[PDB]
Image 1 (cartoon, rainbow, N blue to C red):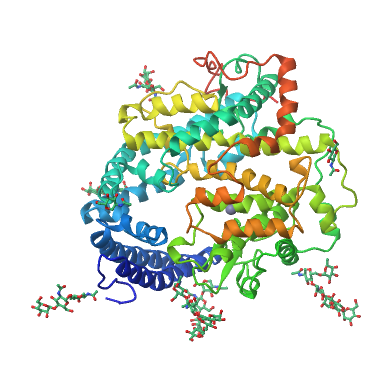
Image 2 (image 1 turned 45 degrees about the vertical axis):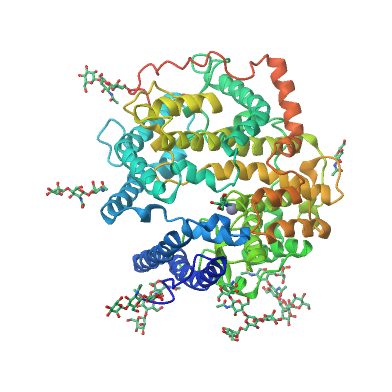
Length: 616
Ligand SMILES: *[C@@H]1O[C@H](CO[C@@H]2O[C@@H](C)[C@@H](O)[C@@H](O)[C@@H]2O)[C@@H](O[C@@H]2O[C@H](CO)[C@@H](O[C@@H]3O[C@H](CO[C@H]4O[C@H](CO)[C@@H](O)[C@H](O)[C@@H]4O)[C@@H](O)[C@H](O[C@H]4O[C@H](CO)[C@@H](O)[C@H](O)[C@@H]4O)[C@@H]3O)[C@H](O)[C@H]2NC(C)=O)[C@H](O)[C@H]1NC(C)=O
Ligand SMILES: *[C@@H]1O[C@H](CO)[C@@H](O[C@@H]2O[C@H](CO)[C@@H](O[C@@H]3O[C@H](CO[C@H]4O[C@H](CO)[C@@H](O)[C@H](O)[C@@H]4O)[C@@H](O)[C@H](O[C@H]4O[C@H](CO)[C@@H](O)[C@H](O)[C@@H]4O)[C@@H]3O)[C@H](O)[C@H]2NC(C)=O)[C@H](O)[C@H]1NC(C)=O
Ligand SMILES: *[C@@H]1O[C@H](CO)[C@@H](O[C@@H]2O[C@H](CO)[C@@H](O[C@@H]3O[C@H](CO)[C@@H](O)[C@H](O)[C@@H]3O)[C@H](O)[C@H]2NC(C)=O)[C@H](O)[C@H]1NC(C)=O
Ligand SMILES: *[C@@H]1O[C@H](CO)[C@@H](O[C@@H]2O[C@H](CO)[C@@H](O[C@@H]3O[C@H](CO)[C@@H](O)[C@H](O)[C@@H]3O)[C@H](O)[C@H]2NC(C)=O)[C@H](O)[C@H]1NC(C)=O
Ligand SMILES: *[C@@H]1O[C@H](CO)[C@@H](O[C@@H]2O[C@H](CO)[C@@H](O[C@@H]3O[C@H](CO)[C@@H](O)[C@H](O)[C@@H]3O)[C@H](O)[C@H]2NC(C)=O)[C@H](O)[C@H]1NC(C)=O
Ligand SMILES: *[C@@H]1O[C@H](CO)[C@@H](O[C@@H]2O[C@H](CO)[C@@H](O[C@@H]3O[C@H](CO)[C@@H](O)[C@H](O)[C@@H]3O)[C@H](O)[C@H]2NC(C)=O)[C@H](O)[C@H]1NC(C)=O
Ligand SMILES: *[C@@H]1O[C@H](CO)[C@@H](O)[C@H](O)[C@H]1NC(C)=O
Ligand SMILES: *[C@@H]1O[C@H](CO)[C@@H](O)[C@H](O)[C@H]1NC(C)=O
Ligand SMILES: [Zn+2]
């Protein structure tokens, strides 16, 4: 048994715990490196050969965590909370979390394979017309593309139900057992249930209470936005299917999960005549190419006097669709090998304005890793799990502005037209604000499941109850206790929390408002840029530098000034769209909210016979 993989002898003392932690850090980064190294190899070079390695390196990592966790859990758990330095408590607290590993091996297999099956079913789920069609439609491209692009209610419904039938129905039996074993494992760790464990990451004694108050402060913005989309859908589909006072059919909102309303912008766009300024056409004539795009992004960070990329980045990063033509996970991602000496971005970059914005986002993560690279490995993560995304986003917000684009040189004049930016801001409002209630209700639901507030006979009653109460949606078809629509969202059977994204979105604008205030800027917040503001850069740098050492709330108070999340900065960013929508809503007499919730559409006249009929 490798000494580099198994812990030694240590007393229950802080001096012992310090020695143990230090030993954990040294071996831990070694282990993490191997796992990610093969991961990067396969992800950058898609082949079954590397997949076998990826599986092997990840397997080793768990045995490592079990060895150290095993010793830690037995050794300090009776005393650990008393260690003086919170720094030490944080490291030990992370390692002492064993999770599933606690299960006896017979249950481990049952729990582990079970999780594997849930993932298979979701990705495997196939939706087939009630005809012996030669080939069915998978989640993407066909199902997502047809649902995002199609606008024939009859057609759109059938695709939506088919997905929930195929994905949802088979997960329901399995998910109960996962609930049983998952909570069983965490009980041995010391959490009342899986929910208590997920909430534990934010170190907020009133965490769930905090979110409700945040969400109630955003609801005025959401209801106004919801009312406007409801009206627009009514113009397109007709009163038979959109009750001005009631909830919106879930399948008509432009995406399989109604989590993003981005695809309906074409119907709702204010001031439809102003074109969205796309710099692609100028970018091409400028001779720019993917490789230069990244150095352009670095220049922005250098303007913020943050750390410029290490040469290791230019060497490692997989900036393009490789000319070798070997397969790659072209979906852009940012990687940090816990090896202090390197960090890499995988973009598969192609020259579009969107990717320019995307590259800035990804480079923000790299910047984030570099600033806390000095901390011990257990702390080299976001201040809170949602904190990581927020930093990446705020950087992306600043660069999207035409004010910034002119500074880079891609634009001759910064036309200060309110119709142009409202057009833009509404697309963002459809893209992300519509997401908040959804991101909140999924983890709102899951804590209920793990907590038992939703016993098994209610998996679907509560999901639609919650989904309607918060998001303002009801199902396209009456659905009952045989179903398990929770299983229809990727994050559910893959057991990945959603709350991180909701909290991240509030933190995104909360940081943004802080930097603008630091940058001496004034007036419209959505016209703010942090470029060249070194004094703001130092403030941002501080928040990154702390990593996970300091409790997330304590750091946030130093940055923005408030010990907790708040909606006020987010609202100010959207002040213009808030003002404009209310007038549009006020004129039409929209009922803000959704009384008479117990209303939903009739079925299509010949459903499912009429599902392919031309209606455009
Ligand atoms: C991605 O784009 C990279 C950026 O290219 C620059 O920016 C774009 C927007 C255009 O304006 C382009 O014309 C720019 O060069 C690109 O890197 C560039 O690659 C080109 C070749 O494709 C290189 O051209 C050579 O440049 C040198 C001079 O550059 C050095 O010195 C100047 C100062 O004098 C510095 O400002 C530079 O930064 C460099 O340090 C020339 O000596 C050489 O001249 C040759 O041609 C002329 C006739 O035109 C002859 O008289 C000479 O004798 C030579 O035969 C080349 O013109 C360029 O160096 C390089 N940029 C930089 C900054 O080094 C990259 O290739 C693109 N990548 C991909 C994958 O597409
Ligand atoms: C978590 O675990 C890892 C692994 O143990 C620790 O990583 C080490 O971090 C230290 C610094 O904290 C690194 O030390 C640096 O080494 C450089 C030389 O490296 C070469 O030489 C050594 C042998 O001497 C070889 O082993 C190595 O492979 C290289 O060939 C120095 O140049 C550095 O100088 C800096 O520090 C000195 C003081 O030490 C200053 O006076 C200088 O001004 C300069 O700032 C430095 O000494 C070490 O290399 C890292 N090892 C690994 C494997 O990454 C983490 O630090 C640890 N986390 C915590 C919180 O302890
Ligand atoms: C941590 O230190 C402990 C000692 O406090 C080490 O445990 C001891 O390890 C040795 C082998 O390395 C074991 O030896 C065996 O002892 C039995 C009698 O106990 C004897 O009959 C055998 O022939 C053999 O000599 C010993 O049992 C074991 N004792 C205990 C209490 O664990 C341990 O190796 C150290 N662990 C690490 C990770 O460094
Ligand atoms: C993408 O991943 C695959 C799998 O890891 C890599 O394929 C392997 O590449 C090496 C050389 O690049 C091959 O080794 C060579 O094989 C020949 C024939 O036996 C031998 O004459 C050489 O001496 C050397 O051993 C290897 O066989 C090949 N395949 C496998 C399964 O390992 C590929 O290189 C990766 N591409 C990139 C760009 O990283
Ligand atoms: C995850 O899903 C797979 C697929 O449903 C499960 O594997 C299957 O598990 C069952 C028993 O749990 C095996 O049943 C056996 O089938 C053979 C005929 O194939 C029959 O002769 C035996 O009497 C028995 O009924 C089935 O073979 C097995 N399939 C494979 C490919 O191994 C797996 O058990 C599921 N995991 C969990 C935790 O539910
Ligand atoms: C939950 O509600 C679902 C409806 O979404 C009910 O499932 C449906 O149940 C009916 C019968 O109760 C099924 O129709 C029957 O089909 C056969 C031919 O297959 C026909 O001969 C009968 O006359 C009748 O039309 C329907 O296929 C079935 N659909 C699904 C998706 O299950 C279910 O009964 C409800 N369950 C509970 C516990 O309330
Ligand atoms: C330390 O132990 C004492 C005595 O059991 C207990 O009162 C105290 O709460 C512990 N410290 C922490 C931080 O829980
Ligand atoms: C655009 O015009 C408004 C007029 O009130 C002004 O407040 C805003 O600062 C202007 N933006 C820029 C970038 O000049
Ligand atoms: Zn990101």
